Image (tube, rainbow, N blue to C red; front, top):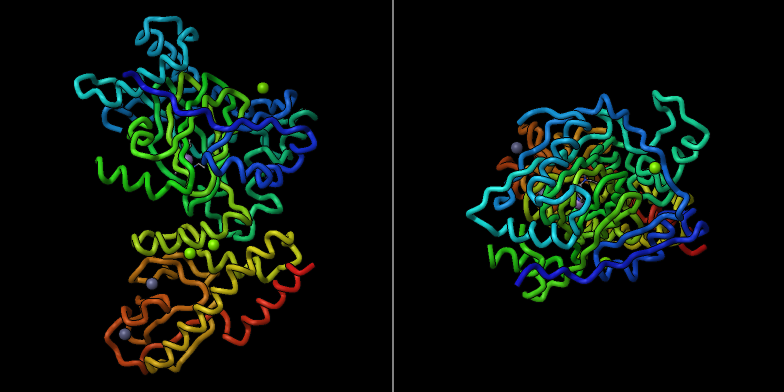
Length: 435
Ligand SMILES: CCN(/C=C\N(C)C)C(=O)CNCc1cc(C(=O)O)ccn1
Ligand SMILES: [Mg+2]
Ligand SMILES: [Mg+2]
Ligand SMILES: [Mg+2]
Ligand SMILES: [Mn+2]
Ligand SMILES: [Zn+2]
Ligand SMILES: [Zn+2]
């Protein structure tokens, strides 16, 4: 049989009232939408931000994609001309007369076709800092119309959403670009993105500025490990293969002017129906905090580097309880409580090993490469073990036996807070959450 389209993902059409608070709205729809992993949001009809990129000074070198296996520079105009001619020539139809179902069926046939070499190009992962965002920004080099200044401050503006009140990553003001600053995607027909989840299992929000639709596939976070097991066992991967192995999949065609939200640890993939322009950014919420906690341990097991420290994030929020709504205060206290108990255990174990010397360290002021456990590559914040005779070495307190062979008298504790200081932080959170 030909490709079977998965069931359609949920589509949300917020009122103007609902639309005022993006993170509030997303929190509201989450119980339904997280059952699907992705969802589509259609803004009120007259919410229409003018495209802000200066088209004539936008240049890029797209990546080469051969469809059955997962280099000139272009301008936006010349990429589009190439894109349209390719589609019209391949389908032998007018460029805007090809049904999305037809493109979709042919895409998945091609991905699995060893004999045919269809190759396309994708302007993927373009920094919005390089040429500007698709959305207007306040401090722009462009004279903003009154209309554009309002869109510049909108919470649904992807430059603004990650620094909103209840956007948790705003508390880490280390730059960590790639998570806080939007990325651009210039697509042509068949240009694709493989199955993945976001850094630190964060949300992503995705907006299609213009062009032909972007076709999405999404998997609920609950089925994340099952998907990974199916892929390991049988091996990008056809959604039909996933569904026939017990993994739920949804689909959608994201049209111009529509948002797509990917929820924490929701696997997603897709391809573009034609020439288009999209913008995306990560964000993190109160309800994401447990996923963030778990992702650190997942990274640890994999010896992957962290973009940021979960410990540091929790403690920075805990230090300012009055900036937290009751939902966030509760979530932070939950995380903080077990962090403190683990730290009490780890420091006790350190004393039993014989280490007695200790120095206070403001880890958040160090570069990441001076913060990483040499064993599990995690970013230290609350504490670390170092050695006076081995200056390059550093381990987190979960790995005090993996620093060096020197005697206990030459090793010392580097700590952010004393054990005494931590109950006070917990108590302040608890009082706040009890308001
Ligand atoms: C927030 C965007 N971002 C930022 C880091 N990348 C540059 C690696 C991402 O990784 C998004 N994840 C990849 C992706 C790509 C697309 C796309 O090409 O349309 C759609 C959804 N997800
Ligand atoms: Mg417009
Ligand atoms: Mg939990
Ligand atoms: Mg857990
Ligand atoms: Mn993504
Ligand atoms: Zn470690
Ligand atoms: Zn040593």
